[PDB]
Image (cartoon, coloured by chain):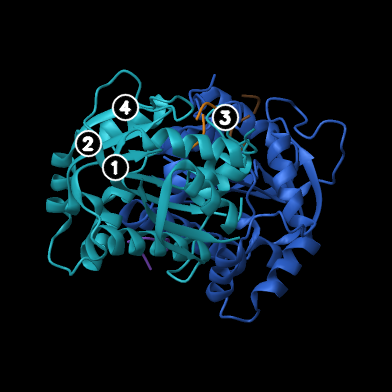
Chain colours: A blue, B cyan, C brown, D purple, E orange
Amino acid sequence: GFTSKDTYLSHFNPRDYLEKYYKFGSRHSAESQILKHLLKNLFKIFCLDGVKGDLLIDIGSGPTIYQLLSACESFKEIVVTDYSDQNLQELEKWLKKEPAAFDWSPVVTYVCDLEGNRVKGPEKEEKLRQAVKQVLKCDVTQSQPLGAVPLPPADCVLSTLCLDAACPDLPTYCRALRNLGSLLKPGGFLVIMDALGREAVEAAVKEAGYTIEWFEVIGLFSLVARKL
Amino acid sequence: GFTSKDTYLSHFNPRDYLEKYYKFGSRHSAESQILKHLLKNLFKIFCLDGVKGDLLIDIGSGPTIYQLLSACESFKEIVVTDYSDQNLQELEKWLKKEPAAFDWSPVVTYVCDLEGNRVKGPEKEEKLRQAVKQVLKCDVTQSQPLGAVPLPPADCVLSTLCLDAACPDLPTYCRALRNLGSLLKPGGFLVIMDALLGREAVEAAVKEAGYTIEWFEVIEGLFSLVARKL
Amino acid sequence: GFFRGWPC
Amino acid sequence: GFFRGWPC
Amino acid sequence: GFFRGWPC
């Protein structure tokens, strides 16, 4: 079903080391730029376009909170989810503000900048932590991706860079999109940001039971759709 | 008697992902300050303090070449070594200007500017590439650490951040240094840059291993030293 | 499993 | 370059 | 194995 060979059962290798400590200049500019663009986009989508409401569920959060920073200004509660328990544990270190946690400061600062500096870093981290109520295992191959955990239907489901992490074939992707629908209220928003064939993604989202409102290249794409 | 559990047998973990892709900073970050200083000291040593010769051996090169950039100014031949073949593959791949090689151009260029900004990156990379003729296994646990390869005796042994990567005990470190002595002419230089085994132990170990310290500087701390084999 | 996401 | 990142 | 250096 999936083509990516990069998992937490891979062994660390010399290129991983090099990329942690010696990756500078053009390769790393590109990453900062790609990430700045996503952040702007989520700012657009959540703070400017009025994608808002009571409950947002992030599907495939990874060990990452950058994708929630603007969302927490528009959603009273956020639920973070991922299949991998190791990812969940990394997120938890940060939510419970443990000192072994990863330092998100310069990403937090950059989002406060995008929001007209209404707020300083720590206040922002506090708003996010207060907004995240649950950290849950999710399995999108199942009709109920959250298992025996019952949530009211969400106003929005967000999913970031999952196609790029796993390289699923199309049907696998289409069926996961459908299974996610089960978490979403009718008319609720689906917001996807991922790596890009444009029409293949489009057809998968339609077939999964959604109407596309907006699609944009920023090949990194961004897409807002609505649950039928 | 090693303490470090960071190896190529370790699994990639989520924190590894974070560090590769979601770390950002400025030239004033701690991490960047350390690398700034390493590069400054290697420049000072091989370009300003007189450490030069025909042949230098880098012991524990990992997959890395930044530690040789100033060194190729002062040495005709460089030999790069590491225990792990996987590190060796990164080095070979760069030395052969293969397109899968890591891109060091930003560090190369920085080093050019530090040296009395003259040279542009491509010439520096060429000179280093001309300088290295051999990429080899090393095991400093053995009295003949390059094994059966015959090498003329060398004018300098270099080793950077091997304590930091392995966390050996004092006796293991000692033995390693004494075995490196075998590769070096009488009076040849040993150059070490590493992290803190504290100051007195590092000195004691270098003395006992059979070397006289001429320079030792400290800045959790990053040290740098130059010594000669007796 | 993947760095983010399915079983892997 | 020697840092991340205005790039070096 | 170590990132640079001994058997690990």
Q: What type is the residue that disc 2 sits on?
A: Leu
Are the residues under marks 2 and 4 on the same chain? Answer: yes
Find disc 1 in the rendering and name its residue.
B186
State how many labels appear: 4
Q: Residues within 10 Å of mark 1 (few under 14, many from 20)?
A: some
CB atoms at circles 2 and 1 under 8 Å apart? no
Are the residues under marks 1 and 4 on the same chain? Answer: yes
Residue A32 as seen in the image, left or right of residue E2:
left
The chain identifier of the residue carrying mark 2 reads B
Are the residues under marks 2 and 1 on the same chain? Answer: yes
Q: Nearer the viewer, residue B123 or B169?
A: B169
Q: CA distance from mark 4 to mark 3?
A: 31 Å
**Picture coordinates of residue E5 (x, y %)?**
46, 36
**Picture coordinates of residue B87 (x, y %)?**
39, 32
Find disc 2 in the rendering and name its residue.
B95
Residue B101 as seen in the image, left or right of residue A102:
left
Q: Residue at x 65, y 57 (%)?
A: A68
CB atoms at circles 3 and 1 under 8 Å apart? no
